[PDB]
Amino acid sequence: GYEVHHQKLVFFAEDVGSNKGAIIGLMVGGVV
Amino acid sequence: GYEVHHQKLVFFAEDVGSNKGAIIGLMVGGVV
Amino acid sequence: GYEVHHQKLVFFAEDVGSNKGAIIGLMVGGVV
Amino acid sequence: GYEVHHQKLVFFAEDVGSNKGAIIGLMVGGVV
Amino acid sequence: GYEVHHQKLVFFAEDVGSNKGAIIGLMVGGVV
Amino acid sequence: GYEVHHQKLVFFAEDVGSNKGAIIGLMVGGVV
Amino acid sequence: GYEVHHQKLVFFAEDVGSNKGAIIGLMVGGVV
Amino acid sequence: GYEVHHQKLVFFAEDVGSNKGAIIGLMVGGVV
Amino acid sequence: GYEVHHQKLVFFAEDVGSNKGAIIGLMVGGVV
Amino acid sequence: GYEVHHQKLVFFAEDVGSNKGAIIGLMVGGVV
Amino acid sequence: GYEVHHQKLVFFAEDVGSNKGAIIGLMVGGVV
Amino acid sequence: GYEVHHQKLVFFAEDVGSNKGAIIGLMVGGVV
Amino acid sequence: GYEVHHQKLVFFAEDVGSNKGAIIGLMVGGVV
Amino acid sequence: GYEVHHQKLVFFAEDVGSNKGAIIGLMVGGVV
Amino acid sequence: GYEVHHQKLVFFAEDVGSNKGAIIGLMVGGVV
Amino acid sequence: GYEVHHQKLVFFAEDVGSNKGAIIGLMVGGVV
Amino acid sequence: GYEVHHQKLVFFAEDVGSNKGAIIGLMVGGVV
Amino acid sequence: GYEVHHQKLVFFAEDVGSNKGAIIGLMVGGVV
């Protein structure tokens, strides 16, 4: 009937002084 | 009980002093 | 009853100093 | 009292934020 | 009736001292 | 008549044998 | 007249009452 | 009268004609 | 020298009462 | 004699009584 | 003179005890 | 030259341990 | 001295194409 | 001598016979 | 602290006497 | 203080007398 | 100091008389 | 005080009597 469930991902990374290629490649959405 | 759907993604990265090439390639699904 | 769906992604990346250093490609299906 | 259903993308990267000093491509199919 | 289901996923990594490639390749979706 | 289940998941990598920067290739979603 | 490779996709859905939330998006680029 | 290899997708939803609500997008690029 | 090699999928959804927001996100490759 | 190979996937789904998100996300193409 | 029959796959999903989101994500192709 | 016949597959999903409704994420094809 | 970064794809195939009506499509985002 | 990273894709194929029917799709996304 | 690394892929294949329909489909980019 | 890294992939295959369907599907880029 | 990290990969295969489907579906890049 | 050398990898394969199956579905990248 009624249910509440969300995702929770926290990705934290240290890498100061420029990483070898900073890029975000994501497929987000699909279902509202 | 209320039906609630959400997503939480936090991507944090330290890359201070200008990155080589910061680029975002993302597809946000157009579904409501 | 109330029905609310959602999505939320926060991308945080440090990299000050770069001039004109940002390339973004965002594509949305049909209707958010 | 009103149901809500929309996406939230916070693309935060240190890469200038003055005037048109970046490459941004936004595509939406028919209706947002 | 009543149904709540969530989980905290946290990833922390230190890779300082020398650049090493920062890229997010991810599929976030599937169902509400 | 009540069913709620969650768990805390956290991973931290510091002072490892050899860097890694930040490469995330993952499929996260599919189901609620 | 020998038959050759044709595509076959039948998407049948009983969705009478087609209002605000009914969207069809077809993307191709090459040959038909 | 000659058999050939071509695409064939039947998208049938009960409520054809598309009116003040649903959105249909046909996109190709090459030859029909 | 002629053979019949192709994919075939029929996706059928019954007499629902019209969903919150039904959508066909389809990419048909321009190949032959 | 003649070499013929073909796919055939029938997906029948029921979701009556109250809307719940109906989505066809498919990639059909690439090769003949 | 080699002859090979094709495969057949059928999948039927009823409403069940209680509706739950009908979404099909499929990659169809690969070769011919 | 020996004749080869493929196997047939049929599946019905209903009255299981936990309602699924209709969630299919698959790679169908590969060769031929 | 000076750093160098450029694309290099040698598509060599005995199967050229620009003729009476072949299909060639070359496209870019914003800047190179 | 000084040298830096670059792409190098050599696609070599013997394919004579192929005429009045070639299709090429090349796209770039991400200032190079 | 200079990085000297290039890509190198050599794809060699025979396909003489006209292919069913020679197609080159690729994305060349990913800002250096 | 010199660091060099590279990859060499040579894929060689015979397919004479016209292949069923010769196609190159390649994603080349992903910030070097 | 001086460091080397690479490997030679060579693959040769005989498939004369038309292969099932001379197709390259490959992802090369991501980050370098 | 760590040093790694490269290796030579060669693979040769025959497969007549029954087509080999020349389709490359791979991913080479991830990290430098």
Image: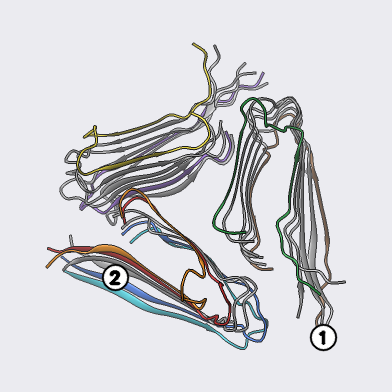
Chain colours: C red, D orange, E blue, F cyan, H yellow, K purple, M green, R brown
Quarter residue E15 falls in: bottom right
User: What is the x, y in percent for residue F26?
Assistant: 51, 64
Between R8 and K12, the residue placed more toward the observer is R8
Cα distance in 3D space between marks 2 and 1? 50 Å
User: What is the x, y in percent for residue F2?
Assistant: 18, 71
Q: Which residue is mark 2?
A: E5
Subunit bearing disc 1: R
Residue E24 visible in this rendered orientation of the protein: no
Q: Is residue M22 left or right of residue M10?
A: left
Q: Residues within 10 Å of mark 1 (few under 14, many from 20)?
A: few
Per the rendering, the mark at residue R1 is 1
Q: Is residue K25 above or below residue E4?
A: above
User: What is the x, y in percent for residue H27?
Assistant: 43, 39
Q: Residues within 10 Å of mark 2 (few under 14, many from 20)?
A: some
Label 2, secondary structure: give it: strand
Subunit bearing disc 2: E
Q: Is residue K30 left or right of residue K15?
A: right
Between F27 and F21, the residue placed more toward the observer is F21
User: What is the x, y in percent for residue H17?
Assistant: 24, 32
Q: Is residue F15 above or below residue D13?
A: below
Residues at circles 2 and 1 in contact by the CB criterion of under 8 Å: no
- What amino acid is labelled 2 in the image? His
- What amino acid is labelled 1 in the image? Gly
Quarter residue C11 falls in: bottom left
